[PDB]
Length: 118
Length: 244
Image (cartoon, rainbow over all chains, first blue to last red; front, side, top):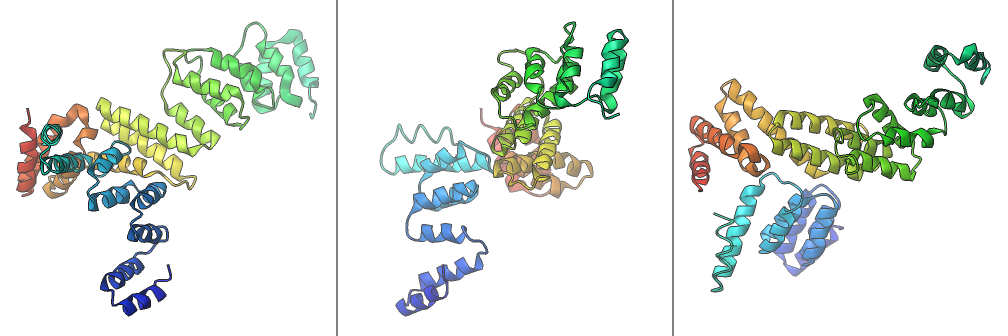
């Protein structure tokens, strides 16, 4: 988490994704927030989710799972705790899982959803 | 004077008059575990103030069970005093016994669960105090008393905050939702339809947290969303109303 040598080395690679990510990370203003961001950067999604949960942030764990497609994970997380808008979030999760099963021609599984969702 | 038992020697004398032992306790009674008053009042089956007089020093483990032995509220101040007695950080098994007693599975008529929160705060195990607060507030919210639930949850939140303790996000979310619903009534009362409509949208997005008033509140939301001009939200909420 130097964010200065990292930016220079990203410039060397001509990696604009890395430069922008480092700039966004520096704009962020908390450690263990940046640590979660960097452990998400490398693809350790389970580690990032556990990190977010340990710092008592179900919100950002939900957001990380929602940027990805792990909607079953969103249902599992929504089962515990409370959120700002959980009915809409769970309806979105159920509709998305219905789409997930229906795009694979797996009806009678998408039919299970689309009903818990509306 | 500074006597451990001389004035109470005269008070066990005076033909062991009760009034003397009732009054000496208020200002200052004795020392050395205060056992003298402990057996003085425990006599004649009077098993109530002996516990209070065992709060002086390490004689509490005897009449703490007697306090606990009552399945019903023999005295509420005695209940709080026994909660403090557990809070003396003795870490005895009678702490677990009082936890069970306040649960009331051995009783059948336990009192309000706020005493459980008080006991957990005294024991300084703040991972369970927050959970008990959440359970109590959620139960009161489900029952349909949102004002009482908000009041109790706020007071418990302030009790946890006063010790500079990291309050869990679940407690903050519950307090935020309850307070938003509380502010719905205020903002509708003064006719400010935009503020009340925003708060009603926030409530309706969690309407499952308000089970017993799912149908009424939602209706109000639509009306408010019609007044404030949030007609798209009104249409969505009314469509959600027309579920069977």
